[PDB]
Amino acid sequence: VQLVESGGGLVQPGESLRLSCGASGMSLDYYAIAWYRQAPGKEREGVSCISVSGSSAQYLDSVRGRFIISKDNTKSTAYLQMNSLKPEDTAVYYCAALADCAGYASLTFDFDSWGQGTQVAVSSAH
Amino acid sequence: NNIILNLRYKDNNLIDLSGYGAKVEVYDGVELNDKNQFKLTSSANSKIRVTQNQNIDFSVSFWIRIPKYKNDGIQNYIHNEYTIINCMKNNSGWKISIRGNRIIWTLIDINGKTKSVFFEYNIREDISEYINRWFFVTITNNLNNAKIYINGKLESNTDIKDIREVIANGEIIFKLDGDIDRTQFIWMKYFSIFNTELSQSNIEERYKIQSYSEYLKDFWGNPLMYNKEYYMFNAGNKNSYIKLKKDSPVGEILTRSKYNQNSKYINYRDLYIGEKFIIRRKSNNDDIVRKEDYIYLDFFNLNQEWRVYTYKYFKKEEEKLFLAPISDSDEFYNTIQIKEYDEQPTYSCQLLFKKDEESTDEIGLIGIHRFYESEYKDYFCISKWYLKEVKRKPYNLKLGCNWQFIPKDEGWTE
């Protein structure tokens, strides 16, 4: 029973990246998926959360319209599509499987100490 | 009914509902909520001024929540007395204040003579009923005595035949005043004043009335919430907590760590430990958990929300609860109805497993039980035995099926 992040990378402003949140041992048919990001050594923050049904999504105000969260039950993986990436998006991204999106942003997962996560960095060549 | 000041929350403000319309000034530094709670902080603008109408034996009642001492600032806590409520005119009147674990009531007559009466709560208990938890204070004064009541029961009775006429006309200031730390604050709720000496009977009735709610409360005395992290407390096993057993789908019971530093004056058991639980509604409009609600009890296992289950068909009186990922299984029950079997005020609640909402069939209540391996160990459990016990009167506060939820709170640091 593992829930693991991948798909991070290093890119230029404006470019795209697609994070995946893969569930092993269990199925996301009952789970609402949340994404969090933490930059060193800033406050960790809730990024997005998609409902169990997948018809409702929540976004951090600074990523809305750039990021798309989705969930594929048949593959037991959920995605964070990250478009128009900006330097401020540089972070380690972590995911969690929740009963419900309500209250997601203020949950206190100790990602730092046991999190795996996937690294995202945005920097221009100029 | 003998009430001459009744401070209550209306329209994001505090208003005298006594009928005498004292004016009430709530400055910007006073935090207010629609649960009638207000907070006095260290800030200069954290203050409430009320002016009594002059055309008006007396009592003061209110609920208070006093944060825990810091494990760093115990000396300041024990020695630095600070005002919270002051009522002075022509250097006469009354005043409530706090020095550490002591809440004190002082009178000062027209000559400047002084008497006092205090309630001090223990600061060495493993689990305290007072520290950083809402409790009810009532102070009564007549010709000869000043009494303090806590939660409806008499605690102190000082003689004041010496102390005569005192002035209560003056403006009442709610304000932390003394050599306080920056982080010092106080929560207050339902402040009232009476032109009579209340009887033990009146005070106990008021205690029950102001305790009642449709909703359950958390360990601190605040309303119990959905979608909020809680650690779990068992009132039948105070120093025990639940932990998911490594490589087994069960919750083992462990003993709480205690304060582990050098102070002659203080002791407590750690509260922020064991699994982080969370309550989820089973839907059929605020996030408040009400009595008879059907809920899911979950907890966080790394980055996964897991859930508390019971086997549908088990043999004995008691069975270990099943802890596992959220999923539909017709081998397990997952729906919990949260209860309040206690007729008397408590922050405990109980957790009933049922077959379905519409069935009157009861499986059992969540508790803690000893089980035999191959040795003997406590586990997070369901028991059918609780079903009859909770029906007994008076309600048994010490039953293992009494649970309380402890969220992180700024009044308690460990």
Image: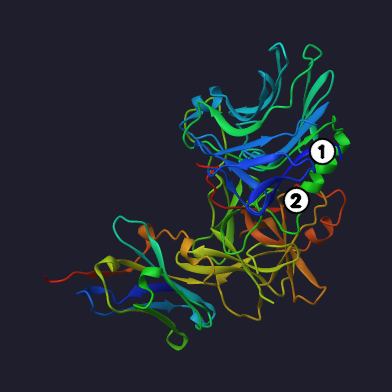
Q: Position of residue B374 (x, y in %)?
A: 61, 60
Q: Position of residue A21 (x, y in %)?
A: 39, 76
Q: Amino acid at mark 2?
A: Leu
A90 or A6, which lies in front? A90
| Residue at the limit of the structure toward the bottom, as seen here | A74
Residue under pointer 2: B399
Query: How many marks do you count on the picture?
Result: 2
Q: Position of residue B47 (x, y in %)?
A: 57, 37
Q: Tell me the residue at 54%/22% (across/down).
A: B79
- The vertical placement of B327 against B21, above or below, is below
Q: Decide if residue B235 is on the left or right side of residue A20.
A: right
Q: Secondary structure at mark 1?
A: strand
Res B3 label: 1
Q: Residues within 10 Å of mark 1 (few under 14, many from 20)?
A: some
Q: Decide if residue B340 is on the left or right side of residue A19.
A: right
- Indicate the quadrant where residue B141 lies: top right
B183 or B351, which lies in front? B183
Q: Amino acid at mark 1?
A: Ile
Res B207 label: none
State the separation of the CA atoms marked 2 and 1.
39 Å
Mark 2 or mark 1, which is nearer to you? 1
Q: Is residue B15 visible?
A: yes
- The vertical placement of B385 against B203, above or below, is below
Q: Decide if residue A24 is on the left or right side of residue B134.
A: left
Q: Tell me the residue at 85%/43% (across/down).
A: B205
- The vertical placement of B70 against B355, above or below, is above
Which quadrant of the figure contains the N terminus of chain B? top right
- Indicate the quadrant where residue B142 lies: top right
Q: Position of residue B352 (x, y in %)?
A: 74, 65
Q: Chain of mark 2?
A: B
Q: Residues within 10 Å of mark 2 (few under 14, many from 20)?
A: some
